[PDB]
Structures are given as C-alpha cells and as structure tokens.
Length: 48
Length: 51
Image 1 (spheres, chains in turn blue, green):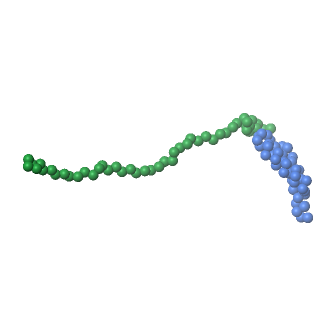
Image 2 (tube, rainbow over the protein chains, first blue to last red):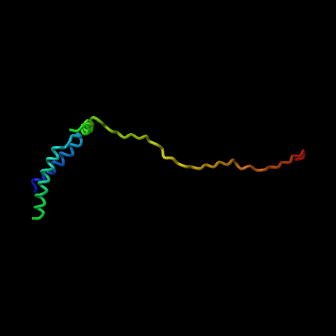
Image 3 (tube, rainbow over the protein chains, first blue to last red):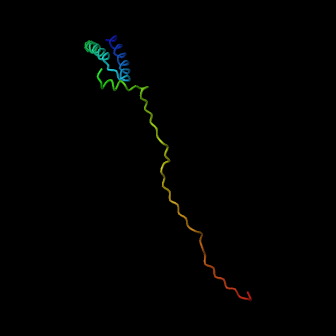
C-alpha cells in the first residue's frame, strides 16, 4: 500500500504537468488504473 | 488527440502570457470651503472750520 502510495504522489506531480501542455493525460489515466488497484489494496489494508 | 484538445494544447505558458495592468487613481474626496469678506463698519464724520 505504501509503495503504491509513493507512485500515486508522483502521478499527481506528473498531472500537475500535463495540464500545462494541454496534452491529453492517457498516461495519467493508466497511472490512475494502477492507483485504483492500489486503492483496493488500501481498502484491504484499512480492514486489516 | 482530439481537435479541441490540440487547440487547448496549442496555447502554452511561453506561447501566451497574461499580465494585469491598472492605472493609479487619486481617491475622490469631498471638502467644503466658505469665504466671507472683511467686516465693514459705518463711520460718520462732521468737519467744521473751528474744528
């Protein structure tokens, strides 16, 4: 969960960047899918 | 990439720079001034040869 969280914070930094270049954030969406998996893991962690 | 996204993508921080400019304006003030001339007095003088 911690490893996924570190990647998630970076993804946010990358997004801060995509908006400036008006570039579509497909990569960000892929990262978001990974983040969603991480979030599911986080929910399990929360239960633990 | 969609055409609308490309139009948004075409604009760039270096490409378009926005600067806000204003002109200094003195604050409006209301003042009342009253002028009234020096007081005048009535004088009566009688002159005679003996005086």
